[PDB]
Amino acid sequence: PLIVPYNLPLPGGVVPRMLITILGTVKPNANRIALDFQRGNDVAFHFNPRFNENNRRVIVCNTKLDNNWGREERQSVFPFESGKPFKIQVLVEPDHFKVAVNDAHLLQYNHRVKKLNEISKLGISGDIDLTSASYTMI
Ligand SMILES: CO[C@@H]1[C@@H](n2cc(-c3ccc(Cl)c(F)c3F)nn2)[C@@H](O)[C@@H](CO)O[C@@H]1Cc1cc(C2(C)COC2)no1
Image 1 (cartoon, rainbow, N blue to C red):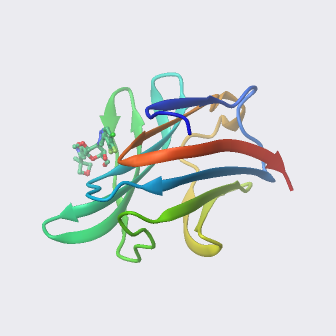
Image 2 (cartoon, helix red, strand yellow):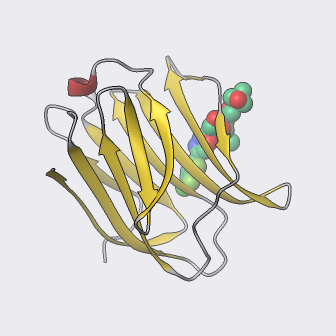
């Protein structure tokens, strides 16, 4: 393992056909996980599984601009389980990030931040044991 929080540099930012893979295990009494694709202080793409928001499991996605959170996009499809190994795959496409978990499509998130080549860090945090974080071009 690596110990969270972990920052993965994305040198020169991201580009369509770039596949980011995050392997780890959800901790047994997990409350939250976050991935933060950052352009400086802005968060181009925040991907935030919540295990107990009002006693429901929900995925919240958003963007932070000038330290202000925007409109949330929410999904009840929730593929994570406390205590289990996971794989998150974020595929950069021309108009969106595509997310699959454990080889099943989960969601798309339209690019609000347009300068993909300045989204130069991925922060990984929350209630996981982190096994690896890496990228390849498909
Ligand atoms: C309470 O702050 C959350 C955010 N958040 C989470 C974390 C975080 C930290 C550490 C770990 Cl380890 C982790 F896993 C984490 F997720 N940091 N920040 C973020 O999720 C955000 C997503 O919109 O919503 C909350 C903040 C929020 C929303 C709104 C609205 C007005 C509702 O519609 C927009 N305003 O403020």
